[PDB]
Image 1 (tube, rainbow, N blue to C red):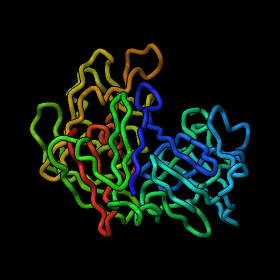
Image 2: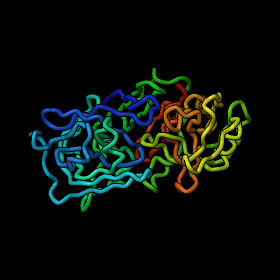
Image 3: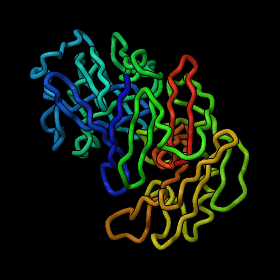
Image 4: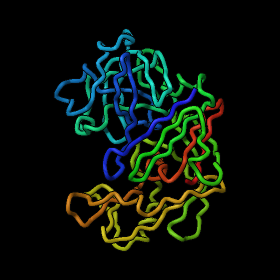
Amino acid sequence: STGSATTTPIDSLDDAYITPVQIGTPAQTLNLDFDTGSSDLWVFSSETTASEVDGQTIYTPSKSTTAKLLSGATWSISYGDGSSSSGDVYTDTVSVGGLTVTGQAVESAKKVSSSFTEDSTIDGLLGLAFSTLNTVSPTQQKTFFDNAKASLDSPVFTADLGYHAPGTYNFGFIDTTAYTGSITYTAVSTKQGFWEWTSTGYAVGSGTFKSTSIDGIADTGTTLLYLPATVVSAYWAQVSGAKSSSSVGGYVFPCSATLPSFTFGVGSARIVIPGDYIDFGPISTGSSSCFGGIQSSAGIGINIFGDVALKAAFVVFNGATTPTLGFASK
């Protein structure tokens, strides 16, 4: 089997991407944030505290003939941005882009933090990291990809995120029309539950490539590119007037600037992030100070190849017995 679904930016900045997902019988379609940095599929639901729902579409398990309470199971998750959610668990039929999993754990939110409430466009998350990170207790549950894997034509999914435009998540096949040149594959460590890999270096603009190992995670659920302070300083030093602002919470730059590209290495291959991808617009409405798309990972504890980086590439998440990651230009 295979699946193919379009993923759409939630706003004009590509803060996140939503992908329609069919849950239950008859189908209830919710727009979920596919997140390769976590491993829970959770939804706003009929059980979510009413004051914490503000415009989201909810899953109502009582209206699904295939929903079954997973008795005794609870979940609770905290994300890198400080947001969180928790609740109980049902199993139900879940389909993405024509690919159907029966008996998928669907984690029903009883509580969500303010960041989720305030984002009317995201109806929940669909985790695509390794199932070892799943938070269901006392019986850990598998991700949608893990459940689908044996039935897929090939044990892979691909992320093809757009810049200010829709893109695609495919399951079970590599669309050879979706990228240019060849795909370069690189080793993955699953030791922390992430799609963790090591970039071979970077360049700023038309500058020379610096060969240096940068361990980080491929994370579709993080907006920006978070890299070591040395790398980030070298980037922003090429933008007149850019500075790190503790009050704003990262590097800012004059909105009048033209940003340089940023290149990252994948083995001997190179992925180029155009300068425009690094512009996250005015810090506040009407400001002439703009927020940068490359930020320091210092104090996160991990480097994160978030959407800013991933949307510059066609990315293969290879879930073979020894997982790997592939990157192509597009």
